[PDB]
Length: 182
Length: 194
Image (cartoon, rainbow over all chains, first blue to last red):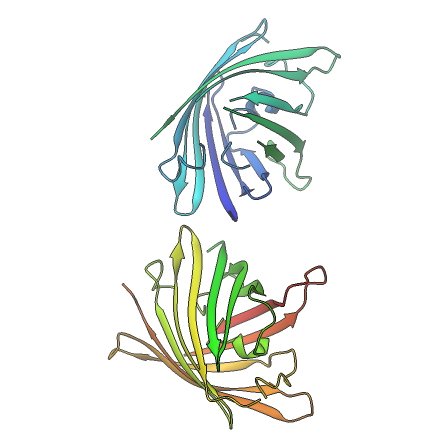
């Protein structure tokens, strides 16, 4: 019910970086509007690879609040490196906070030759296994196998995502619009 | 800080006429703006909407009382007509500010029940004065309601406040949702202190 504020903090790693996301969420319509900012400068990684790691609560995840849940993922990129991520999503003074730690390859990913977009997927829902198709600039696809577990402190989720850019923003950033349904 | 959701629930009972109103919307203390849609769930109101405006926050700009929120009790004398008696509790419920109100009306005549008021609300400054006696706040003010013929209906408000744990100027616009068939009131309000 209603629209809640969202804080997202991603501390990433031979290249250290930090991303802070701020925006609003509306569970009534299942809409996300978020702007992410690279505080440490340009990312040594393409933005679409951080999309999945960067709040399923908007459509268990809701019942987990306000003490919230822990989300851990290991993400294998085909013929490349892998992500390992741990996150804590919970409520802090009427604001939903997602604190994330991820650690990682060869220079599609470090090469920065992906397309700035993100295709829709059905997620098999806690445990989860799914594969994301990233569009590559040449025409090929970069596959990313996700393994996911959840823990509190049988259905599907379809998600649609739009990646855009704030024109009057000079820091490396990502504006994100997302619709997720059950 | 930020924009908070608002739930307003008023179970009312005037001269034999029971009614329930649910208001939903947003509040922003930073700019002092209220956006609310009120719905008469029990059907057409036995009372004109402008007479419920005062009773239906003041926290936006009352703030210190949250989240274990204050009690607001009012006695509202309509000139040569009936009177309102209201008790309300404004507080936070899961990040939402809720204003549950109980109102009762006695000794009316059929401006108010006659439904001959204008669908609008003139601005007023409210005289807010503190009182350590009841650990709360008191206020007295009179609202001039425009009646359709040309005259005015005056409504004398007496108000006390108390926690469960200067001036205020208000500006109000009353409108209607075109795609809403229930008896309702769209409300926009700007409130500042002095």
